[PDB]
Amino acid sequence: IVGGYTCGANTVPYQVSLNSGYHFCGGSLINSQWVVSAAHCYKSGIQVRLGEDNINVVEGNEQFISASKSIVHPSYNSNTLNNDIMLIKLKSAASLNSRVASISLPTSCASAGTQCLISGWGNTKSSGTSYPDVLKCLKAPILSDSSCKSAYPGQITSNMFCAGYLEGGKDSCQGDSGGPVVCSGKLQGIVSWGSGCAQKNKPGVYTKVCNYVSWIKQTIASN
Ligand SMILES: [Ca+2]
């Protein structure tokens, strides 16, 4: 996250870290046994880390649970990033409380102008690299589809939205991928892609979760 603030320990209780020996992506806990992330975060051998603030220090609220199954969306296209969404089933159910909690799926899509919370452990610089150990947060609005398509001609599908600031300076970045965009207490987006981070006229692009609720519910019900 570039241009954000330190969230505070366990203030984003649905935020997960995906770990394969090191943090490589975020995700969101949607019930006691399932995490949603980006398809471009797929790899084998994922451990899901819940209850994290500092990802390099054991602070006492962590739960580390291995993945038993990963399901990339059937229509994911790695070249265009269309349908950039993946479900991960945990080997055992997480223990839910105030510091580890699920986030609700949306019943309707959010409109442009809605303010959302984006969070992650990704790079905090737009030029150069500095990775934080504690969770960073950013409040950002959903942008109109016309502004999003004007920023990224020929690249925005109906399964994507832009959020952030056309003036630059505040954005998600490398290592935030797969993490949550939460608006009015519902998961509306997944950190997906962008051209660089926090550049002028290049806001972040996010997977539009409301288009996937039927697929998520049907998949969880049968796996
Ligand atoms: Ca920790």
Image (tube, helix red, strand yellow):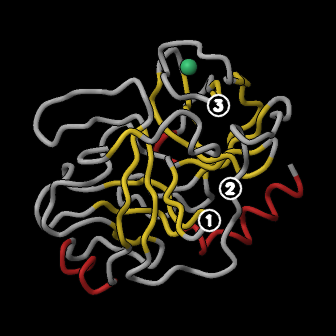
Residue at left 58%, top 13%?
Answer: 58
Seen in the image, is 30 located left or right of residue 221? left
| Foreground of the two, 223 or 112 | 112
Q: Compared to 21, does 34 lie above or below?
A: below
Q: Amino acid at mark 3?
A: Gly
Any part of residue 71 in sight: no
Q: Please tell me whether mark 3 sits on a helix, a strand or a loop.
A: loop
Q: Is mark 1 within 8 Å of ligand 1?
A: no
Query: Dots 2 and 1: beta carbons under 8 Å?
Result: yes
Give the Cα separation between the discs numbered 2 and 1.
7 Å
Categorize mark 3 by other alpha carbons within 10 Å: few (<14), some (14-19), many (20+): many
Q: Nearer the viewer, mark 2 or mark 1?
A: 1
Write down the quadrant of residue 73 in the picture. bottom right
Q: Which quarter of the rendered image does ligand 1 occupy? A: top right
Q: Is mark 3 within 8 Å of ligand 1?
A: yes
Q: Amino acid at mark 2?
A: Ile
Which residue carries the number 3 mark? 51
Write down the quadrant of residue 85 in the picture. bottom right
**Total numbered labels placed on residues in the image:** 3
Which residue carries the number 1 mark? 185
Counting from the top left corner in percent of width and height, residue 151 is at: 18, 73
| Foreground of the two, 56 or 190 | 56
Q: Compared to 121, does 37 lie above or below?
A: below
Give the Cα separation between the discs numbered 1 and 3.
18 Å
